[PDB]
Structure formats: C-alpha cells, structure tokens
Amino acid sequence: LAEKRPPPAPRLTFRPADSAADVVPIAPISVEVGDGWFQRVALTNSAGKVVAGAYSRDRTIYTITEPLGYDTTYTWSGSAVGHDGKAVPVAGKFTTVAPVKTINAGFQLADGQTVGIAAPVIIQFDSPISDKAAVERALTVTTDPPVEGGWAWLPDEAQGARVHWRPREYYPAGTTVDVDAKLYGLPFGDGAYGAQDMSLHFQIGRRQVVKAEVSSHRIQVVTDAGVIMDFPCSYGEADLARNVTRNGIHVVTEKYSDFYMSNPAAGYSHIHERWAVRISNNGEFIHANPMNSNVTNGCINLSTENAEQYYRSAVYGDPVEVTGSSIQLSYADGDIWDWAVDWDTWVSMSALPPP
Image (cartoon, rainbow, N blue to C red; front, side):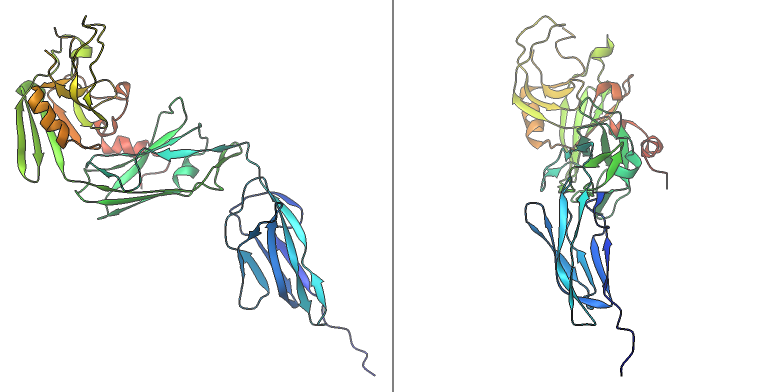
C-alpha cells in the first residue's frame, strides 16, 4: 500500500538573511515561502513596534512597505502551512546599519514661501560629503512650467557641504517649484548616511527686476507694469575696492526697516541706516541715504522716501542687475553670487556630467 515520497517541505527564503547585519533601511525586506503559503507574518523592531508590510496575491511573499530605522534589530514572527497542512514557524532576525554619522540637511526656503525670479534653492548640509555625485543623483526638481536649470556644488562652508539649484534664466513669474531629496538610507561616503528624506514646495511671485547702471546716477524698478520706480541714487564712490558696488546680477535676500550701523572705516559710530534691502553678504544694500565716501561703501543710496518705497516692494529672490562696475560679483563677496557666473561654469560645478 502507498509507498510514495511525501510532498516537499516548505522552504523559507529571508531577504535579508537571518542574522544579517549592516542592512540598509531602504533595501528590499522580505520573506518568501516555497511549497507552502503564509498563515501569518509580521516584522517588529526590538521595542515591539510592528512594521507595515503586505502579502502578494499568492501569500507566498511578504514584503515590507515602509522604511526601517538605523541601528535597529528587527525580528520575523509568523507561520507557513505546507502541503502537509502542518505549520512551520516563520522566525529570524536582522539588524540595520549604524552609520558612522548621519548627515543632516535643510533648505533656506520654507514650504509655501513666495520668492523672486532669481531665488536659488540652497541645500545646506551639516557635514562634508565624499560622494556628492551620489547625493546629487538623489535630488529632483520639478517646476510648472518646466524650466531648464541645474544643481551646482559650491565650496563647503564651515558648517558643511552645500548645493544650489538655479534655473538657467530667471523663473517665469508664478512658477511653482517642488524639490525632493531622497537622502534617507543613502550612503554619502565614508560610512555616512542621510538623516532623512526632504521635500520643499514654493513658488515664484511677480516679476520685478532692478536696473542699476552705476554710471547712470539712477536706479529703475521694472515689472509687468513697466518702469514703476525711477529714482536718483548714488553708487559707491569707487575710490577703493570696498567702495565699488560689485558688477553683475545680485539677489535680494534679507531686508531691515530700522537698523542703524557702526562704521569703523568711515568714523561714525551710529550711522542711521533705514529701509535697507540686502543685495549681497559683502554688505551691499539698497537703502536710505544716511547723510565721506566710506559712510556708505558699495551701497546704493536713495532718499529715505524712495528707499522705503523700494523696500516695501522688494522680495527675497529678486534680481538686481548692476552694470558699469569694474569689479564683478564673486565668491569672495559671499552669497548670493550664483548669477554672477556663466551657465557653462554653473554646469561645471555639478557633481554629474553635462548632459
């Protein structure tokens, strides 16, 4: 009677394998059974928190559907039924990698922020990065309308590495911008890993461009409504390099309504400085005239009344186009100098090829 080999016994395949270590928390995590189906399956961290997962139709595969944490031991629990009708346990463990250090990052813009047509997207990291190419490949920018641009790595700051995204030309007014940085579980190099995924949504406000020909004694503000401000103004006397308003496209960043300054080189210890729009970290403002050539260095001086009008109109990211100056805006001036370099140079600063 009978005399026939029994059916195959269920075989469990753990990916990652049992007692595996240095598992990347974003890697595919799964258990598969052959010659049987899963009755129950679950993955928990050491603290007992269940991880989301799902079976395939056949219930012969269970796959984790959310990212894991770093430096954490996970364990499988459950059972699989074989041809026998007999259940076998589903058990095993693995441990995710514990990075030498986690590198953090942030944007300089807030979600929902409206900025001017020359605003860069600045990602500042809290550490140097070895595989900047790998990091950059994890960045994606989406604009509406679509717009040509590129990522460029600038010299590391004291705090750490940094990459800017710039469109080739000024943004169309109204453009929406979505930035995604899939950095979690990404190896940055030398055993470094990204702290987390990051996203940014912002948008471009109205088009406003400042025309600042240094030899013109004027400054103009141009929008869709045409020339809305045409002011007399003075530029830096240009007797010293510090007194030369730098040439090239500046970006408006911060502005201060009242903030009266201490100028050592001029002689005054309490200069009344109002309605000041910053156009460079080197100290260039468009501001009210305080009144000596040192009292206002490379600044653009307006009447207090005109200065306030421009001040109230100005937005972070606005371009100020300085022309007719001897000294071109540079890295030596600090941020933002992104628009003071040609496109081919900007492309060259990418950690990736052209295309």
